[PDB]
Image (tube, rainbow, N blue to C red; front, side, top):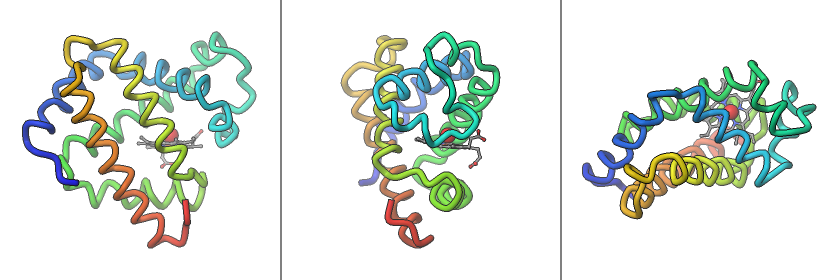
Length: 154
Ligand code: HEM
Ligand SMILES: [O-]
């Protein structure tokens, strides 16, 4: 469960394209997440009322939230596995305050992969998607371990 440097470079090469417009990517990822797995939207007290994709796209608060998620995830990815410090606050808030199960982290990982596959075929072929999946699996494995330490089954 340790990524090679070549795998990390495939992850970071597609993430650089995400960074051309992190806000737009965040909107697409949230829309995909909520339309593939509607139950996840219920965890968001401020966004749970959104009824349609048009409302999600027009929500300035949701756009800002997407930027926060992707920027936090980008900082984790750029540590190339040395993300202990970054996972501490994230694991605590998601376990104890938002109460986000591991299955829901799997759902957002799937939404990320789906959106990168659609938007970035030039940097998200099979090998690149495999590397991104490995990076997200590592993130989820380490978050799950921290969840257990914090008292949350997940
Ligand atoms: C890649 C995985 C994720 C990352 C990097 C991430 C990151 C963040 C960050 C940085 C924040 C703001 C600070 C904080 O409260 O920690 C946040 C808030 C939040 N997260 Fe996540 N998150 C992820 C997955 C999820 C998922 C899958 C859900 C629910 C299905 C979720 C639910 C929430 C909620 C409800 C908030 C508070 C939102 C608000 O203030 O309106 N998170 N997340
Ligand atoms: O989030």
